[PDB]
Structure formats: structure tokens, C-alpha cells
Amino acid sequence: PDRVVLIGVAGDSGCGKSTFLNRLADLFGTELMTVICLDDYHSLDRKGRKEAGVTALDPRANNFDLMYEQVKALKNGETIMKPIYNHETGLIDPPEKIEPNRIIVIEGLHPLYDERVRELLDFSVYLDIDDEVKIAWKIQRDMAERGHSYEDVLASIEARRPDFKAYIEPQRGHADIVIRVMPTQLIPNDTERKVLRVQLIQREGRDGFEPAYLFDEGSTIQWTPCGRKLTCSYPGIRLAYGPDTYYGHEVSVLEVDGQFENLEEMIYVEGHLSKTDTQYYGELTHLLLQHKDYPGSNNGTGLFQVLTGLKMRAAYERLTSQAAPVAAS
Amino acid sequence: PDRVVLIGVAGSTFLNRLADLFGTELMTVICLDDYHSLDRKGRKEAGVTALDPRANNFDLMYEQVKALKNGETIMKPIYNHETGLIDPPEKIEPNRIIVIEGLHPLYDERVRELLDFSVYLDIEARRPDFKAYIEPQRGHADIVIRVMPTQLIPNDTERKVLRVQLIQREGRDGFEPAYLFDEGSTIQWTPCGRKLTCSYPGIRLAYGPDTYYGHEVSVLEVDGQFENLEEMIYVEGHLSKTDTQYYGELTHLLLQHKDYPGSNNGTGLFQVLTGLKMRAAYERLTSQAAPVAAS
Ligand SMILES: [Os+3]
Ligand SMILES: [Os+3]
Image (cartoon, rainbow over all chains, first blue to last red; front, top):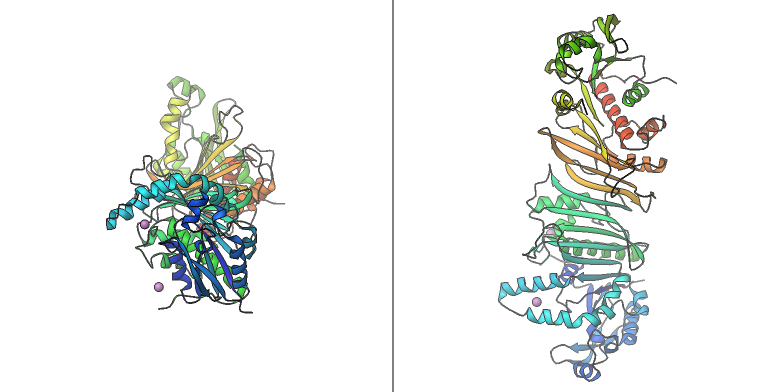
């Protein structure tokens, strides 16, 4: 059976605008993977939302019944006629023809919201970014190309909180992996807002998914690779691993704080991680340095985005007994 | 050549543990109080303590220790602690291992160079002379076992739970320090978790490079108490370059005599580990198996 694998990606970065999906495209290519933006399943257009007094985050603005049916149909090998939500006009355009593929990624705000859709997913990721980090990034991006559109991100964050906490964040409890970004604990008065502390919160007991760990599985460790063999500059790099309870479930949290200045630092860290699901030594570093221009390229953000990708590849190859798709040259 | 190996021990249950490891047939222990140049009355007369270098004959010490390592029999004096007198010489023949024990095994430069391995054990009136003449020997010891109060219990009142440090000297050829996880990097570890259930406050290890008396060292550290077997073995299994000859030898040797003090904490663990590092040093120098206790 030509099996269709389904991947869910929860996040607030907008459709086609996250670096994680670019990294997935680098890994799996674009020929045998199709990405579906879940804003296409809005039951209410922009005017309709205003009329109703609800935001896009509200479940009532979204059609989960149609979502379930068309995603179920795709996994069952059927072609679908899915709607297109135009973000510019704020209208719902005529359906698009989407055929099945080896991998189907559903991306958006509510991929893990409905019980029925959850059960169709084979792997899932929630990208949890701290408000302050999101804001600091927006200023750095604005600084580069002279955009100055960060005051609207601030407005958006504050006003979204109620609906974000109500309907978006609880999906973290159902995600296999949660990449959690937040400010550093290595620097006392962080003014630059550059150095990040990132957590890979991995769900236990999901058959066909072995969490990555450091040193000893199921025990708690704090590690600093800087020392005799590796020279870092202040504040350096610090890892942490340990078991924890997240949304009432057992998880295994792998954590990196700091910035990678160079190759040696990246490989030294990669080499000492366990069950990273790399197919050869140095694949994370190799994949991470593929596109150094991406944000998070020199810290835990990129590292864990890539690592998550490998865990999907593992899941795919387990379900199909076949090699996963790859990007061309 | 029937080579004689020399071990120095500054600062005991440690020697009992060594006797358990190496036996008493092929190891002779020499108490360094036997090389007092001044008897108890002489010390009073001079106004010095036993800790003072002037109360001790390092020239005779060097010569007789040098002679022992060279395969010669010696006629060494006996210092009677009860009467406080120096009795007639004792005949001591060479042996596979010679341990010199006392306050000043690492004090003299000439005696230091004869030693193949060395240990300092760091567990009111003595303080001046202790700080003046005893403690600086820590800077020359290959291993220093350092005991101190715990950091696991806030406002510790019992004073029972201990934090112990195995400070291992780097660059001593024929001695690879034990480490945890990654050599030359800093780590803090707690084995209690999914696989191991501890009772409060549990156990916590730490390893990392440091500078001690101006030298590079590698500090392995345990804080807490071992309630049972499983805890001891779990810790042992995750240590690296412990110089055990089989899995579970530390635990086995540590539980040999549970009645000893430090039996259920880092004190005993590191006493045994230190013993293994001596065995390693011996077997490297002789290209031969070290002595063992009978059954
Ligand atoms: Os932007
Ligand atoms: Os390449």
C-alpha cells in the first residue's frame, strides 16, 4: 500500500512564513511533500468574523468537520477539492485540486485542536515562542531591510492573549515534540536579546518515537561542553536534559542555552547527544550549516528544528518500511 | 627485576580497605612516626609538636625507603606511642608493595620522587602546625579525598549527609583520572529519576576540570547517601575510567564491610576507587598482577 504519512505543525508564524517548514523542505524536498495551510478551512471570511465578533483563533471561525473529512480522504488516497482562503482580500476563493502525496504536512493554528484530526496524525510539532523573543526577532529583521513593522506585532501579541491561551496553547499537551524558545539564563542583564534558551520537550510512550537524550536516559543532567578540549567565549554554551511532567504526561526535556560561534562547537555538542536519529555523524551540523542565513541558525532554535525533522523522517521510515523523500541537487 | 612499588598516604579505615584489596602478605605498612628524631620528652624540651619537621628525621626516612625500593633489608626504629620512647630497630624486608603512612610522607622533596602513587585524606591547638606543615602536602598528592558538609539539605542540622570530592592530579603518567560522561568538561548529574527511586534528599554527582594548588586537576564529587545496592551500582555503572576489572567491583568491595564509617557515602566509594587507581599504577609498573586478599 502506497501509504500517506500525516504531519501536524502548530504555530503562530503564519502560513509559508516559518523557517521550520523551509528546513523540512530542505530535508524532504517539495516534490513528494505538499504543505496545507489550515487557514483554508475558515468557516467565516474576514467580514464574517467581524460580524460574529470573533478572531481567526476562535474555533467558531474554523470548519473542523470539513478539515477532518478532507484530511481523512487524503490519507485514504483520494483527491480533494479544498477551499483557498485569500489573505489579501479576506475572501474564500473557489476550491483547489490537491492529490495525495508521500508526506502531507498540515500547518496552522489548530492542527491539534480537534480530537478526530489528532488521531489521523502520525507526528506533530508545536512551536512555542516566548513573546519577548518573537518581538526581539521582529526588530532584528526590521533593522536589516528597513521595514519598521514591529509595533503591529506588539499590538497583535497583547490583544491575542485571551484567545491564544484559550484555544492555541493547550495543543502543546497533544504535541509529540514542543520546541520552546525563551530568553537566556546565562547573562544577568540581557539587553541584546540575542542569546536564546531552547527546550525540546519530547513526549514519552509514543510508539515509533524514541526521544533524544544526553548521557543517561531518564536521569537529570546539566552539562557545559566548554573546558579543556573546547574553548568558548562568554557566556558559552550549556545543555540540560531530564525527565519532567508536561500537561500531565511524562516527557523528556532536552535543552540548549547559548550560541554556537563555529563548527567545532556544533559538532562537539552533536557528537555527545544520543538517539538524535542522524544517519551519519555530523548530519545535524551539516544540515544546520546548509543555510546559515536562516534565523536560529547558530543556536538551539535551528538545532532542534533540524533534530525534529529527523524524528519525522524516522517516523515516516518506520510507517512505510521505505526511505523518506529527499531534496534534489 | 622483582620491582618494589611505593605508596604514600597522608592524613584509618582507608588502610583497612587497602588491606582488603591487596592483602597483608605482600603489602607491609610503615608508620612514619617511627622516624621521630625526638621522643615525647624531647619534643616537650624543644617546644615542638610531632607535626613540626624538626621532630622528624627525613634523612633516615629517605635512606631506608630508598634502600627498601632498591631491594635491601632495613633496620628501622620503632616509636612506642604508649611510653613515648624510641625502641630498638625492627627488621623490615622489601615487599611487592610498601605503604608509608603518617603526617609527612609528602613533605620531603627526596621522598616524593621515590613514591609511585600518593593520597592525602582531608576529612584547635594543632591548627598552626597543621596549616604550616601538613596541609601543603595536598599540592603534591596524586589524589586528594576531600570531605565536607552537604549542599542538598538547606540549613543542615544533623550533619550526617556528606559531600565528598576526589581531586585527581592531571599529567601524572600512568594515572588516568576517573570522570563522568565527558572528560575535561563540567557536569552536574542526578541519577534519581525514572529508573532509580531515591528518598530525600537523594544523590547528586559533579565532575569538572579545576585548578588546585596551581595545578590542573579533575574533580569528581558525590553528595548524598546510598540507601541500597541499586543506587550504588547505578552510580558505578555510569562512571568512566574507574579502573574496575569488572562491572560492580566498587559496590562489591564497598559492601564487603558495611560496618566501616563512610560505607554508605562518597567517603568509602572514593577510598575504594583510590585503591583501584593504586592497583592500576602497580600493574603498569610491574607488568604483573597486583597482590590480592585471600579467601
Ligand atoms: Os516578518
Ligand atoms: Os550538503
